[PDB]
Image: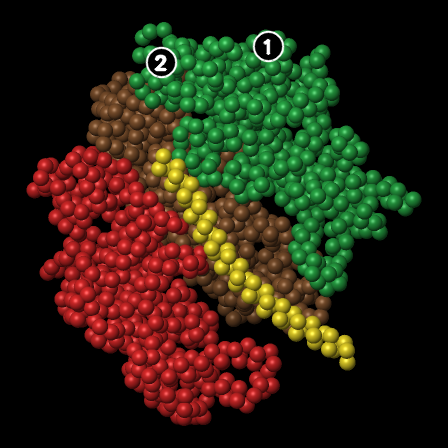
Chain colours: A yellow, B brown, C red, D green
Amino acid sequence: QGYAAEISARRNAMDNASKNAGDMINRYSILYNRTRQAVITNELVDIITGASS
Amino acid sequence: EVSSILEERIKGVSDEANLNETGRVLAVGDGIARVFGLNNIQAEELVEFSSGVKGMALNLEPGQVGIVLFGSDRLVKEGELVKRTGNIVDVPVGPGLLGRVVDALGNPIDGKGPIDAAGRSRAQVKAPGILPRRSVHEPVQTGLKAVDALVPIGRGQRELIIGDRQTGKTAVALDTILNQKRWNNGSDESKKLYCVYVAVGQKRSTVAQLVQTLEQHDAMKYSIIVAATASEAAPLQYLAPFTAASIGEWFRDNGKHALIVYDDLSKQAVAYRQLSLLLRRPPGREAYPGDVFYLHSRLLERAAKLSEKEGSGSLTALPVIETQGGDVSAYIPTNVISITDGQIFLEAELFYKGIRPAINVGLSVSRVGSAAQVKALKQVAGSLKLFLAQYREVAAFAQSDLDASTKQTLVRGERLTQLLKQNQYSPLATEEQVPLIYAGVNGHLDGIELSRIGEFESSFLSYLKSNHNELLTEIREKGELSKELLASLKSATESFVAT
Amino acid sequence: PITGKVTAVIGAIVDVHFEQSELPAILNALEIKTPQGKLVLEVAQHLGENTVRTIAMDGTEGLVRGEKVLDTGGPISVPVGRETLGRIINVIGEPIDERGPIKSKLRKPIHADPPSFAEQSTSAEILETGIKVVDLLAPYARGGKIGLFGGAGVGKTVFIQELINNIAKAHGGFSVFTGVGERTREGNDLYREMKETGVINLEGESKVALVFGQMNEPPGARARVALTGLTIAEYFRDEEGQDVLLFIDNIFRFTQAGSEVSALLGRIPSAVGYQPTLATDMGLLQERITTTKKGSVTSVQAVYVPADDLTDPAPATTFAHLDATTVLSRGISELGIYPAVDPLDSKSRLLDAAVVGQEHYDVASKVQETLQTYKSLQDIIAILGMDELSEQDKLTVERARKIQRFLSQPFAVAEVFTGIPGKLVRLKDTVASFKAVLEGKYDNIPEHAFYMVGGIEDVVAKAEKLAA
Amino acid sequence: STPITGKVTAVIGAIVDVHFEQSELPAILNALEIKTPQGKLVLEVAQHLGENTVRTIAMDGTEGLVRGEKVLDTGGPISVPVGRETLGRIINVIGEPIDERGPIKSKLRKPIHADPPSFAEQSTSAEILETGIKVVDLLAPYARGGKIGLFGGAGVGKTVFIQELINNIAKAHGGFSVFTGVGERTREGNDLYREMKETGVINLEGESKVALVFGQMNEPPGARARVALTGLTIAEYFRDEEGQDVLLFIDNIFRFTQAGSEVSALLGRIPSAVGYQPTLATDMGLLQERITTTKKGSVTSVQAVYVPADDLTDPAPATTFAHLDATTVLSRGISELGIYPAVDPLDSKSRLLDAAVVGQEHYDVASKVQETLQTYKSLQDIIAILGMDELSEQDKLTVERARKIQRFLSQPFAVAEVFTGIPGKLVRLKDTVASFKAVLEGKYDNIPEHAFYMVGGIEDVVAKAEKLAA
């Protein structure tokens, strides 16, 4: 009775895990995207500063 | 005699006429001579210095004409006469350039004597329009089973070979050139792709390897190697794909077929960057010149499958882009990816996992694709696309208590993956592609042990050749698998599996 | 008599020195006679001292400083008319369809003022769209910008074609497919396809007029192709009264092109390398497009989001202009549904209750709620099993799969291609159809009697035929 | 025309502009000597700015200069001395002996700039060096005449590796070698000079099979740039005029890229990506193309490279990565695993490592190693959370084998006796192929995992098995 409950619990738990991980994927995706824009901009600023001189 | 050849050469010098426009260098730094004179200069015209250095005139400024030296700065010096050659950048184009390793100027860097050429055509010639083309309908087989089936290659179309650094990117390409020997041997001009390999920024050691491999596989007699080596300067590097394209255009203009492989535009990018930054032209994204999009787009649109009014011809192209850390995000990759029509994405992990070609099927796409697939090969490999797709999804399930369905997928998938391994620099004829894939499709290979897949393959081929090379000859010539052939083929696979 | 000599050709930025008191204005068009026909330069600065700075629209190859220049006197004036229908025209307003000189009455400057606030139509009205899915879940609107999303692999081209057919039926309109920085390969396909689908029938009549912008064209001409197209549309709308729909291809390539021209002009690029004139350049393009009293343009645009980033400035500016989004998807096409429109991702901002009618809004909301629930149900229907989920739930599943099928429409344009007679459904009857399905009056009729049908009336027929 | 004299006009830094007198035009890449209280300051002419005002780069430190100081022109590129009289001498960039054995007896002199041999001339064969270092031998064997590249980042025991390499390969091969140090620490310098005196390669009596060109990072940015160019010409003399195969060694070539980046900035060029020189590609290219096997000598460069912040995607290492024939990557992670050599097996690659080249047997053994290790790396993420008992049975054996193979790569260095105490094991090539094969075949999968650690070949492993057994 226990063993079935345990393996069942693992199924339930691992399902909830995937969901929690998905949320983190989305959160870090926004972070990635923001960071990506920032790199382009910050690099661009260095180039511009040089060109201006 | 050594005396006689020298005597001919001295004899071949004699007299001259008025040097139309002299210049005097004002300042020469960074290979950017800024010349006072050359009043009537044409844009990007070829100009000859006192030192004999040649240049182009990218900037025609309101009082100075900014020549860019094709040569080293050492030879040029201030106040030099700058004679005006008076001919905009043009390179000999003709039929004789086959089996001639030439640099951008067209000078044989292998000393295979003066170029035989039927025209000198400008390297700035603009691509054929909307209506001067007719949609792709002619395959080009590469002799790589995966390329030919998973991402079929047509004519006049362009697809990337975009992948991780020094994964023997050139090897994947070189294989295609080798397979063109089979079709080349034939007399039909339909069956003649005259390949051009454009070695951009490639070290002379690499070009020596290139030269020997091509000679070894007897490929030189439809090959041209336009060579702009690492040493060769940034104007040459810049104009190197442009020059190459013009050579291709002559073949295309004759209505023939050819395949021009630009390897790699990443080094082309660097050269334009060098030119622009040094000419103080406005910089842009990722410190690549502002008009880098414009450069790449100009080159890549030259490739065209011509219309029947223009007596259908082609200039199939295969640009190679080297990804830096696999970043498709990077500015030069993003631009090229957008411009091209399909990508083949080689993947380092696969290479390490011994899959060679290390093409990552997922990240390989063709936007022309199956439109120019051999009909026979199309028939026997719709299934293959779906199976591999499933194999990818069920890949992670390879860690115990696994459903029978998943396990079925795994067996079929693993065997297929093993089947698509190929020993690089050996191309495989379509008439031998078709049987192997048929077996896999019919899942008779599922039974064969993983270790024995390699042995099975060669054995099946020899068995087919012994058992019925009539079938093979039929496959080759009919090119369309009749029900009787598909029947016979299934039987043959079964029989072979039994032994 | 305004003529000048070229006094620089640094890049494709050609400075021309003009003789005194005969100085072009900003946005004039200069024509340099060349062995390339003409090279059209557009004055984008005055550098003073009777010199200007211009941009190029054709390749700047082999120019000699000292070439005679002639000043047109204002922005390039491109032919307009019903004559110019079915003609592929390049940026400089000359035939590239190679069916000879375009016969035309009047020509009009490529830059044109965006209609005044007075000319604005007070409140947007729906633009009927034959695709039932469009008219239910995200209606088009006359004036509006409705941004198609999802590239080819969804039958994008057929969808674009369908719209061309539909507008002609819908109003009597015309269209102009303008392709900004389109691959020349794709352009060939479109011309061939459009000829085949008879939307362009040179022998017959050609609804759509083509303006094709090849990537080979210099960045300056890449930037100006859109504005040229817009002028054509405005002639139809304003001066022939006909409502039109002006397609744009990648509006990413509009942005991209604009960025280059700025950089060429030496203007410091802004964040993520996008032109300092980023707002204004979209602003001019996307406010000329509007609802006039005379007629209305409506524009379907294709947004090739850069690296699937929506927070990049080019998308952000694009989304500001967009009013509705039609989100074609390949998943949908894999469920055999052509329309390829993804119902749960298609959204309109003119979906607004007041605008679309309360009844229509409520019907749509129910269909949306049904679909939203259906999707969620399908997640656990697959895992748990259909019968292992409520009577109420399978009533919803039952209802849903019928709606899902009901979405399908065999397009009129692709009557030729599929062989299936077309279906064009009027707006009132679209509302009616969903009302009946919501009341489940046809929720007896099997699922596949709804597959690839037209309106409510149509699926009466199919119920009978399914039985027969 | 008037006697060649220049007047300094602006010392703005290393860039010092000189105002040569009218009508005598100095030439691009000439060499100027300015008599100074400390030697002759050498300025390399690099641009003409017109009106007989040149802009030149300094090669020695610039201080105390007075605007107007007479400048003689020695013309053309800096002219070194070359000979076999340069053997066993440390030659500073301008060419002066810094081995302090008094004047180097010059036979011939050569310019420090020379155009790389043309494609037709350049003849390159594939021949195989034997390193006797197991990871190197199996997974990326080195080749004579190559452009071997010791890529690694910070503190990869880079010096330790080099000391071993010189000890094995350099001494073993004849011909000449040229040891060039570009912009390296005087701690590293003092050790390298001492070590090769100790190994007697620099035999203070009798000929030394190596010459030294020590450029250290204390030298001006300018001097750092053209120290590499200087060294290359010494090698060219060996390659050409002495005809002999050269086993060139340069250290560290990231310092060469870095140096060039600096003088680009000083030259006033618009900074390129990550501030590197826009001329980076052609400069890297110029150095590498010059280094080659000709129909005469076979120059075999072994070049150290420092990979900033272990990002080999950074444009400067990445640009170098292409030009080098036989890469070796030493990775921080592998160092921490205690595997010495710290060569990362997955990332080490050499052009020669093909069945048609290094033989089918060698190839097959190495193919088995490569796949096994790659599988093992893939499984590590899975192993991390799920554990060992959730993978396939086959995989569990593969992991055990991989762990055995992984520590078999730890083959002690003979120069790490000094740094630690471990005695090096110089394991023969034929033997190495054999030794790896056995493990993979499972012939020694009865032997514990830890008995592959820090020992040589299979023979050593069996002995080490006995050692653990006791």
Decide: is D93 above or below A47. Answer: above
Label 2 is found on which chain of the structure? Answer: D
Residue B407 place in picture, x, y as percent: 67, 69
Question: Which structural element holds mark 1?
Answer: loop
Q: Nearer the viewer, mark 2 or mark 1?
A: 2
Apparent side of residue B388 relative to residue C38 in the rendered image (left or right): right
Labels 2 and 1 positioned on one and the same chain: yes
Residue D174 place in picture, x, y as percent: 68, 22
Instruction: Measure how far apart labels 2 and 1 are at the Cα level.
Output: 31 Å
D66 and B446: which is toward the camera = D66
Residue B368 place in picture, x, y as percent: 42, 59
Question: Which structural element holds mark 2?
Answer: strand
Apparent side of residue C234 relative to residue C216 in the rendered image (left or right): left
A11 and C357: which is toward the camera = C357
Name the residue carrying label 1: D104
Quadrant where the N terminus of chain B sits is top left
In terms of image quadrants, where is residue C156? bottom left
Name the residue carrying label 2: D20
Apparent side of residue B250 relative to residue D75 in the rendered image (left or right): left
